[PDB]
Length: 251
Image 1 (tube, rainbow, N blue to C red):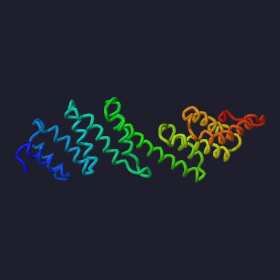
Image 2 (image 1 turned 30 degrees about the vertical axis):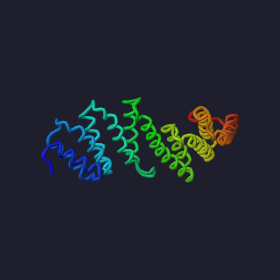
Image 3 (image 1 turned 90 degrees about the horizontal axis):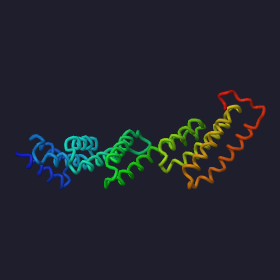
Image 4 (image 1 turned 90 degrees about the vertical axis):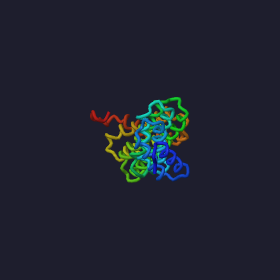
């Protein structure tokens, strides 16, 4: 097998270069049987992380990237390592219908990277990954809201649409979700006892302003105007109704 860190390293690289990642990995690990002080330890650790990655062992990759960063803090590759570690979670991030634990892990990892090295070459890439991961999360919530609305659970729909624009305001689903929330609040109001309607209509009225303030160029502004008009006119009739008293909780 091997007699020195160099033989083990170069054998690992031989396997690595021809895509024999399982074998490479075994040889990178062998390097460390001679300790980590020799001149090959940094490279061995860095390419071990990459070999796991190329072998699609992302959790193992992530751990080894982390170890590289822990051990060799002024190695010029430390920023790359932090980025590629975030990529492990990115690869693990599954389709939006499934549990999004690893999606949230990836986002945090990328965000830390961006905070730590705000001008790094890889920042644009990391930002694009964040946008893509955030869109998954937004879509999951948007589709959930649609299902509630379809089931005529309108309060549930409304707050689930709000999750999209409150938690993920930069995703492409955010303006769609504001409109969806207005529609749901209108429908929630309609199913409500008269005295509890104003505050529900008020929510829809307030969401339109936010749409206008945050997405001034949204194509949905004109679409949503009709919704806003319905909410506003109904709220006016209610507010102008001299015979509708309103308990304190309804103002």
